[PDB]
Length: 613
Ligand SMILES: Cc1cc2nc3c(=O)[nH]c(=O)nc-3n(C[C@H](O)[C@H](O)[C@H](O)COP(=O)(O)OP(=O)(O)OC[C@H]3O[C@@H](n4cnc5c(N)ncnc54)[C@H](O)[C@@H]3O)c2cc1C
Ligand SMILES: NC(=O)c1ccc[n+]([C@@H]2O[C@H](COP(=O)([O-])OP(=O)(O)OC[C@H]3O[C@@H](n4cnc5c(N)ncnc54)[C@H](OP(=O)(O)O)[C@@H]3O)[C@@H](O)[C@H]2O)c1
Ligand SMILES: Cc1cc2nc3c(=O)[nH]c(=O)nc-3n(C[C@H](O)[C@H](O)[C@H](O)COP(=O)(O)O)c2cc1C
Image (tube, rainbow, N blue to C red; front, top):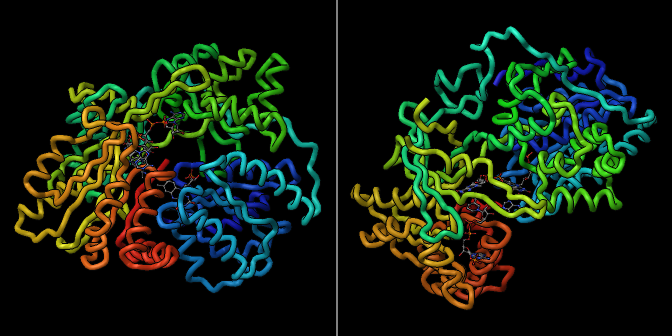
């Protein structure tokens, strides 16, 4: 990872006084940065965004060489309160450096989520650390809560931030407003076909010419071997997929995640085009008007609107306030121009409307286009606004020791009645479902992501796995592997599964496979919880609570490892208590002593989580 030159120097040479580093994976932090960066301009200053992984943040000490200089960090938290991948260098650095940042003015906005225990560790860290080094805080730390509404949290913060800035430095709010574009449109007519991106993510033609290694930037088109329906009932659609990675040299261990780069719904794309009156089959490119930025285009180019809407753009999520504000200009009917503008208010009714009519109603772009017919923006400007389509992750359901040449996926297809009035569909799950094992084959641009979730190294350590619904996913690989080790002579301690589902004839995933593993003995216990076969709910905690005596015997004496995968707002929290209570009873020990004991197993590597909401 060859770093770029002193960003301070670039700022000097490009007349910029504020830089906004973004630490993110799904791009939300990146978005905020770009917004905060563009914002800078309307207040007499000029800023720029930047990936800290491309620079050496050691130069912060040089930043004071620029008048009215100030750095801003938009950081998100992951894993064990860990930084985003790209924010890793920055982190390790802040920890090891002793550098003096005297004269450095900063501000930090962190993206977190209250379900997790390490709420905005990064944000809190950077803010607090930069001070210890010497830099002076120009504005309070921002704690954005995604479980509530990060967007609004950002708004509220941003709104107070600029004035503070303006005041500390004595600068004007320079009239504000009047749309400013980032890219410039360039339509191509002669464009040699063989050089137009068709949905590749990295180098031109990387999808056709597959050359390792394969990473997020160079995914590996994997053939869909099997795509079966796992649920017996019809309430929902749960599926088991098997991606063939032969000849990819891609390594992986049960507990890792695999990511996919899906394609939006054809019909949904056609309509956006149609309702705008634009020819989606036009070949074009959006070159940055700043001939200095490294981000030459909003996405791969040259390409066609259809390709961008289909593979490069997120056209299904609720548009964020700034995208709607920018569009307000393209709505002829005033009534509508107003709502759109108002969408980015910090408070008032504008806020409530953006919160219920857009977010709560899950209204995506096309929906808003249909509901505000006077809104007919230019297709090229829309693409510059829409955010980038992300890859979806999946707990690899298989074990490397048994399926080295294949990755398995257990997923629940997303589909629901939105209050917007229509039916929304999960981008990747709908895409995945439509893959028929069968150019001709069914390929899925994927790539693996290593994780922390891992079976114990020592084959005799007791494993306790709590994974209701699709939470069982990673655990299918766990059991396969522990089954293997036994067929390999290896001595295997207890292996217990604590699974859950509605009814044994609705969503009892791997009812049969799990039946085998149990019969043969691979699974010491197979405690399953049918939450709907009786008046009262029977969740997995109840089972854990039921086996308190035994579990505590492997946790406290057998040094067993606890694994938790699935829902994070409830399932995980409820389970975590039950463990507090098991420890507190059989300890014995007050709640506090127990809560700690558990959290220790958590840090001492014996209690792993892998939840989301
Ligand atoms: C580390 C990790 C591991 C994961 N492992 C798995 C796994 O093993 N199996 C699996 O199925 N998924 C897993 N996921 C979730 C997975 O990545 C996808 O989010 C999921 O498959 C749906 O993606 P989609 O693109 O089809 O849906 P999208 O189009 O992206 O839509 C999903 C979004 O729609 C919204 N939504 C969903 N239902 C409703 C509703 N009823 N009403 C209103 N809004 C709603 C939510 O905001 C949700 O985030 C994992 C995620 C992470 C981060
Ligand atoms: N981050 C990850 O790695 C990961 C992996 C898998 C799933 N998930 C997340 O979990 C959510 C749902 O997953 P899912 O569809 O697969 O599960 P699910 O089908 O919705 O539910 C599975 C089982 O859990 C039960 N349940 C509901 N509330 C519970 C509680 N408080 N304690 C214990 N069991 C409870 C259900 O019963 P009832 O419905 O009848 O109440 C059912 O028996 C999604 O939001 C998804 O993001 C995250
Ligand atoms: C796998 C995963 C792990 C997360 N872990 C944490 C965490 O430990 N602490 C926290 O405060 N937020 C956590 N979050 C929430 C994110 O910090 C939040 O969604 C943020 O907006 C992500 O930023 P991005 O879009 O810029 O990548 C996690 C999200 C995911 C999907």
